[PDB]
DNA sequence: AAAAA
DNA sequence: TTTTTGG
DNA sequence: AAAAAC
């Protein structure tokens, strides 16, 4: 059957047969992100995504026939990798000073594209020179990013994610005993590692005020136990939690990035779908809804622009059915 | 950079 | 060709 | 007042 250009019409499991090609495409996309070339960035991310869905490895140029998101530029990169097992284009990016600095600087929690570009133009090349500088002033987010750097750069494994789930559930049921807590993000998609642990929290009987106060109550509780290392509440919150080694089957603990999302009970299917990801799967779900169905999808609702009506859903399956899409399992959304 | 309009 | 590319 | 966080 014909491979769709949309990640939401493809099954993408964690068995990637084309990592030689996708690692190169991911590097080229990242360089275009840094150079603020959004269009070229997105084209390399889509090409990498479609190759991740293939049930076989590309071994010749003939194998690329009929695969969407592979134009002339991308096919030239694939040809070069088939030639000698390496990408000369990705090798040039890996040796570029601007690219090396951007990767290193943005690896700090609280440092994005703008601050990384600023530090590079100031002549900084190492994290040690940035941290020891007497004129630089750091945001509260960056201070936490540097303080817990080694823990946050080492990423989270499944026993750690599960130990965090227990902490989240224990804290949440203390204030809302009927609340449903679901682990979302990469770990829901079957990943054995991740940069953080994400959760969706919802309650069938909580009031508008109870729903608003839960994240404040849960973070104050952790602050009292000395487990809240960083907190930013937007409803959602970006946290750094202290995970004691005794809770997971040196200092005796590990800093873990945790994100919590609280949503009204009736919108829980839209929120679950939006927070499960992957990022490419989400973008293509919304792109497909707009361009193929004249619908508008977000983390709270699904709207029909022609009929001028909102479509209701109690599950992810009902959202896929409204969109006219075959149901894709969470472990098949690794686009 | 690739595909739709 | 020009426009869109998640929201 | 950008900038960072998904
Ligand atoms: N630009 C983005 C980033 C994130 N998300 C959504 C989908 C996944 C969910 C969690 O985001 P992350 O934690 O940033 O990513 P991840 O899939 O969970 O991967 P990792 O396991 O490495 O954290 O939020 C999104 O729609 N668009
Ligand atoms: Mg995540
Ligand atoms: Mg996250
Ligand atoms: Na960063």
Image (cartoon, coloured by chain):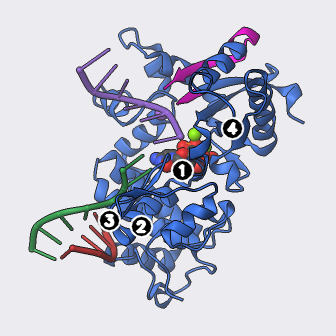
Chain colours: A blue, B red, C green, D purple
Tag nearer the camera, 3 or 1? 3
Identify the subunit bearing mark 1. A
Q: Do labels 4 and 1 share a chain?
A: yes
Task: Assess disc 4: are there few (<14), some (14-19) or many (≥20) residues with their C-alpha within 10 Å of its C-alpha.
Answer: few
Residue A23 is one of the magenta-drawn residues: no
Q: Which residue is drawn at 52% across and 29% down?
A: A109
Image quadrant in which you'd find residue A159: top right
Q: Which of marks 4 and 1 is nearer the N terminus?
A: 4
Identify the subunit bearing mark 4. A
Residue at numbered disc 3: A306
Residue at numbered disc 4: A204
Q: Do the residues labelled 3 and 1 touch (CB within 8 Å)?
A: no
Does dot 1 land on a helix, a strand or a loop? helix
Residue range corresponding to the magenta coloring: A223-238
Residue A224 is one of the magenta-drawn residues: yes
Residue at numbered disc 2: A288
Residue at numbered disc 1: A274
Position of residue A250 measured from the top left corner of the image (x, y, whole percent):
81, 22
Residue A314 visible here: yes
Task: Assess disc 3: are there few (<14), some (14-19) or many (≥20) residues with their C-alpha within 10 Å of its C-alpha.
Answer: few
């Amino acid at each position: 059957k014909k491979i769709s250009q949309y990640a939401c019409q493809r099954r993408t499991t964690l068995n990637n047969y084309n990592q030689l090609f996708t690692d190169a495409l991911d590097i080229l996309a990242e360089n275009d992100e840094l150079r603020e070339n959004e269009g070229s960035c997105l084209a390399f991310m889509r090409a990498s995504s479609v190759l991740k869905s293939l049930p076989f490895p590309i071994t010749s140029m003939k194998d690329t026939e009929g695969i969407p998101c592979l134009g002339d530029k991308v096919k030239s990169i694939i040809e070069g990798i088939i030639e000698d097992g390496e990408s000369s284009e990705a090798k040039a990016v890996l040796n570029d000073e601007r690219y090396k600095s951007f990767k290193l600087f943005t690896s700090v929690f609280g440092v994005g594209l703008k601050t990384a570009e600023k530090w590079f133009r100031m002549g900084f090349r190492t994290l040690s020179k940035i941290q020891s500088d007497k004129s630089l002033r750091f945001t509260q987010m960056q201070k936490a990013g540097f303080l817990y750097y080694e823990d946050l750069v080492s990423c989270v494994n499944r026993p750690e994610a599960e130990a965090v789930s227990m902490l989240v559930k224990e804290a949440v049921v203390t204030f809302l005993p009927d609340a449903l807590v679901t682990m979302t993000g990469g770990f829901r998609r079957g990943k054995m590692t991740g940069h953080d642990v994400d959760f969706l929290i919802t309650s069938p009987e909580a009031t508008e005020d109870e729903e608003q106060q839960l994240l404040h109550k849960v973070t104050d509780f952790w602050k009292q136990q000395g487990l809240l290392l960083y907190c930013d509440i937007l409803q959602k919150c970006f946290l750094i939690l202290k995970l004691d080694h005794g809770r997971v089957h040196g200092k005796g603990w590990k800093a873990i990035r945790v994100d919590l999302v609280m949503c009204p009970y009736d919108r829980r299917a839209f929120a679950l779908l939006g927070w499960t990801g992957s990022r490419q799967f989400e973008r293509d779900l919304r792109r497909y809804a707009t361009h193929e169905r004249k619908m508008m999808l977000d983390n709270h609702a699904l709207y029909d622009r022609t009929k001028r009506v909102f479509l209701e859903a109690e599950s992810e399956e009902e959202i896929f059915a409204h969109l006219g899409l075959d149901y894709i399992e969470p472990w098949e959304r690794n686009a």
